[PDB]
Image (cartoon, rainbow over all chains, first blue to last red; front, side, top):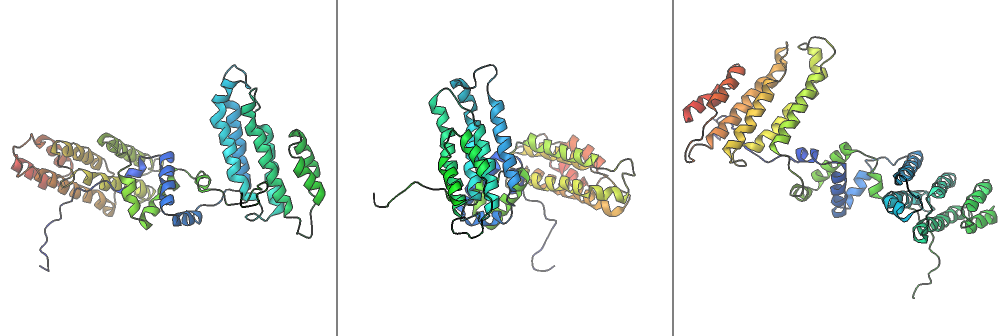
Length: 199
Length: 198
């Protein structure tokens, strides 16, 4: 009767909706496509940020532990662990441990994280994680471990340095860093020194 | 050079985006990504043409699993037609219909011209709808009652695109029969047209 004369509306054959197609795409692909949606729309990163909770320090530490375990077990069957061939096999996994450290550690550094007691706890965990890295016969493969010690040293410094201007200082981990630097073949010297200095 | 650079000391930041999204499974990624398209519609175009489309068989597989998932959701050994059972299953029930609603249109005119294919799908969709669960309360049967109505219209459009077009394929006249007989006859409109066209 009214404006337009109607008669049983027959369905229209439309295209598969967005939700349905995303179902047939997994974690990798989703994640990967999502990372580019943000690259195109930076503002998205803030929303998601306010949507996803930051994993707890313990969660993070638990991740690195799992990450280095993956490495130890990725070593080939019955061969030399310090071997070159044994290296190529674990490379990927190795990089994974390292890439995590680069990600996580900055969360517990000077401007961003001002909590001294926290940051140390993570540096300690982190350094121990680095103590475990695999050595090799070839001097090239070991460069990633020493490099790790170096950068690692930089962080302990910056972390301690926030104590400089800060009145009221705790009882810094002299014994922990002492052993830390020892296991490290003295690479952490500079940090051990500043520790004692400030202390 | 121009700046007096010393040994670089690390600077603190918030763990990168790639890291944060590592502590979330396909569910959340799926969801949050969905909201991104809602706020930035232009994102759908980019994600569309680059995503792997599910084949007919896969879609069909999805439905089976769904209703097979909905059949196990029924409480212990209670009355599978009581109201209580309905609740514990409304959701898994609805999932079946949503999936039907999404996928079915994907095989009608405008979009799908290939008659010999659409019939194939609708056939498998009607069977899914036969399988739906009946209940004592009459209010919980409108969903399945309505389903039958919709697919009726759905076969109509499919059969209609076989009009002005040359020749007349071998219509599933013998198929819709067992379908309309099973659907307690509320699918006759589409079948009366079958014998008609045919």
